[PDB]
Image 1 (cartoon, rainbow, N blue to C red):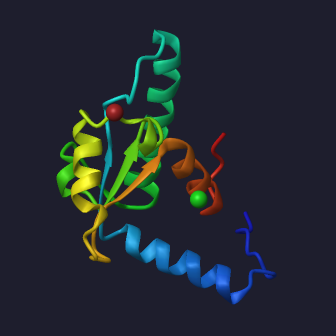
Image 2: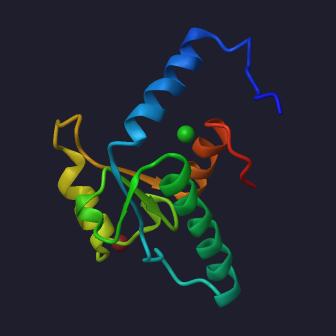
Length: 127
Ligand SMILES: [Br-]
Ligand SMILES: [Cl-]
């Protein structure tokens, strides 16, 4: 059927989308398994299901590589916000190793909530 084509998209937004679509095919993404803090079993299952959906979109629609080693990934998707992770967590230790790297190439850390909004804005029907 007819493909959606937003004739009202301005150049800012269409350029943002174009550059993201191109860049996403070049990177490695990690959907990190570690939770920042304790949560009840049923609440962890809800998060895991959301992480799996994001994984499928990144791998299959956005064409990113998916890794189990977050130290090789360009976008690191977390099961909470970075401030939720304790200093003892390697996610926080690595984040701290990168914080003062003035290196535009360094990894970015996104909660699953932040990631879901990004994917929605890229045109996918997600929660
Ligand atoms: Br802490
Ligand atoms: Cl944001």
